[PDB]
Image (cartoon, rainbow, N blue to C red; front, side, top):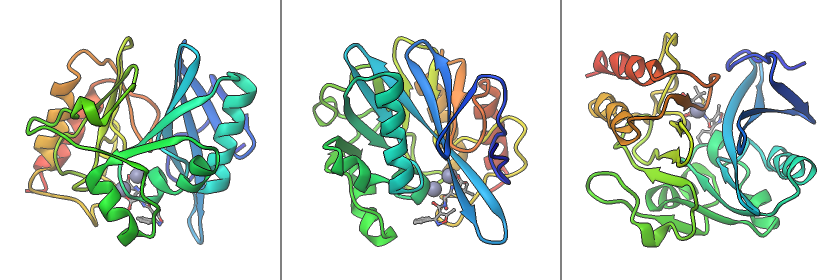
Length: 241
Ligand SMILES: Cc1onc(-c2ccccc2)c1C(=O)N[C@H](C(=O)O)[C@@H]1N[C@@H](C(=O)O)C(C)(C)S1
Ligand SMILES: [Zn+2]
Ligand SMILES: [Zn+2]
């Protein structure tokens, strides 16, 4: 088993599949986890989501690489055997967007914040094929998110990056904070190299307010947590200003 240097460990409830780990969170929601082996440091886990919506599946975030992302698609084919309608990626960094080419080879429509698509080439990423735009209060413009089923996309403001977005899963008590939110026991806010240290706290809190009844908070580098992950992230971010 994979014991990452950074990221949650495997526990009861986890399925190893290839180089990845999958965990069912709800009857129709699974967390995908993939690992980047960094030289001299060991594996860094990154999480995203798989959502069944009737006869189709929706994905939030790629794995770190194209091969890992193809493995996600193979797990979905094995375990669910329904087509992937679209994927939403939550900002233009490798943990979230490093597998875009596997999605595109598979014929899956991809969506990202317009700003993530504008940044991606500068980051050595491939842009998603469609751009999401957002209102002044952070809610996605619904015409840019056609047929998203239960995915409710919200741009909370700059934080981990200027383009980070978040996704609520309607019909469940789950919301996904991506790299913006760290868990309730975290000692750090992770990589702040692209962060907006003035606005981070307010953006973390805005994500909480967008999904006020979400009780299970999913994030990129820890196991799903309570709402304390939001409040503790904001308290850590208050110290950056
Ligand atoms: C590693 C890693 O190695 N190379 C890239 C990369 C490639 C192209 C563009 C940008 C980065 C990368 C990456 O994606 N790093 C992310 C980042 O910087 O935010 C990861 N999220 C952090 C967080 O959530 O705090 C983290 C400390 C877990 S690291
Ligand atoms: Zn990032
Ligand atoms: Zn990250």
